[PDB]
Image (tube, rainbow, N blue to C red; front, side):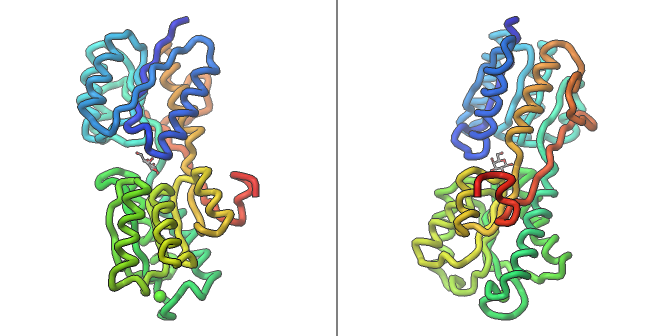
Length: 309
Ligand SMILES: OC[C@H]1O[C@@H](O)[C@H](O)[C@@H](O)[C@H]1O
Ligand SMILES: [Ca+2]
């Protein structure tokens, strides 16, 4: 009756993980037999490690961990193994060797590559439809790219495959600049402001961001320079970003399904806390201890299936 599940969020003010945290809390408030103990790791893996020791001292029956550093998976598994507590890692994917090292380690996330291919197809679709976006009329997309954290599975796959997909759809590309803005709105605004103040400013035709928070910072820098006709694409379909696709400030985004990843994390951690099989009594499909929830492309044409038009 007191099933205790310990949850760490790598940083509470990351925009997307804020949507995921609130949905896990909602699922916990809804289940009368579960108590969730939620922690903000404040983007520090040492802080997270200490929080996991306190959760284990408090007797949690399962841990649902969103890692600060994907490479710390082994440290967390060794803490959990000692007390035979199952661990459901979510959103930052650990290595396969770390997942295989413990039979009660699972992961809930997405297939990262798919969000890069869907973003590439959304760009391809809108580029073909808007020939005026080709400012210098050379048939090539001149773009800048705002990357998430270096080494994060989603940042690396989204950066690689958005361009690979455009080239496979037959659209040649020329990267004018690329830099990391660490998934953050303010850092992205500053980097875009710098590019709009440098020698390439007039040549930028498309802004590609690995997530919506960075797309939103770019939209702010573009408005400040009265360059709001430059299309911006993101990933996550945050409610604030959906507002920008409606107003045309953004051209498209990709739904990163926070509700189902939160639901799957909660369902697997509750089952495992109860000594049942991870997917018992659910529809989740676990393959090799991983659940991957699909990404969905979002633009003005299917916007009504995600928000009110
Ligand atoms: O690890 C946290 C990151 O996860 C990504 O999947 C998401 O697109 C980013 O916005 C950020 O939340
Ligand atoms: Ca061009």
